[PDB]
C-alpha cells in the first residue's frame, strides 16, 4: 500500500492522528513481594 | 445569449450586481505544522 500521514496540512490528502489513550494509564506495583537484605561474615563469597 | 451588465444606468435594461460575500471570509493557517531551520558544516551541498 502507501504510507498514512499524520496531522494533515492545508489541502488534499487525508491523515490519521496517532492513537491517543490516557484514561487507561495504570501503575504496576507488586505491593505483596517481601525481600530481606543484610550483611554478615560468610565462608565463601565475593567481598 | 447576451452579456449581463452590472450597475444599470437611468433607463431600460436590467442588471445584476457582482456577487457580494463578506461574512464568509476566513483565514487558512495550519497552526500545527512544525519545521526546523539551522546552519552547519556538511560534506555535500550548495554553500
Image: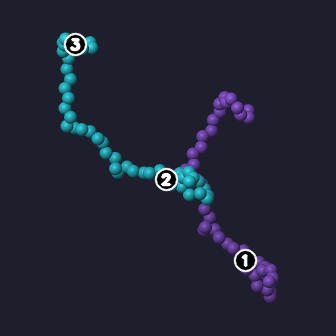
Chain colours: A cyan, B purple
> What label sits on residue A17 in the rendered view?
2
Residue B13 lies, in percent from the top left, at 79, 86
Q: Is residue B33 visible?
A: yes
Is disc 1 surrounded by few (<14), some (14 to 19) or many (20+) residues within 10 Å?
few
- First in residue order: circle 2 vs circle 3: 2
Residue A44 got which mark? 3
Q: Nearer the viewer, residue A15 or B31?
A: A15
Q: Say which residue label 1 marks.
A: B17
Question: Which mark is in front, 1 or 2?
Answer: 2
The C terminus of chain B is located in which quarter?
A: top right
Q: Observer-nearest residue: B41 or B5? A: B41
Q: Which residue shows up at 70% across the image and 32% down it?
A: B44
Q: Is residue B9 among the parts visible in the rendering? A: no
Secondary element at tag 1: loop
Q: Does residue B42 appear left or right of residue A16 in this picture? A: right
Q: Quadrant of residue A34?
A: top left
Mark 3 Cα-neighbour bin, 10 Å: few <14, some 14–19, many ≥20: few
Tag in front: 2 or 3: 3
Task: Find the distance from the CA under tag 1 to the CA under tag 2.
Answer: 45 Å
Amino acid at each position: 500500500q502507501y504510507s498514512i500521514q499524520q496531522s494533515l496540512g492545508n489541502a488534499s490528502g487525508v491523515a490519521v492522528s496517532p492513537i491517543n489513550a490516557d484514561a487507561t494509564l495504570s501503575t504496576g506495583v507488586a505491593l505483596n513481594s517481601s525481600l530481606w537484605a543484610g550483611i554478615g561474615v560468610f565462608a565463601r563469597g565475593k567481598p
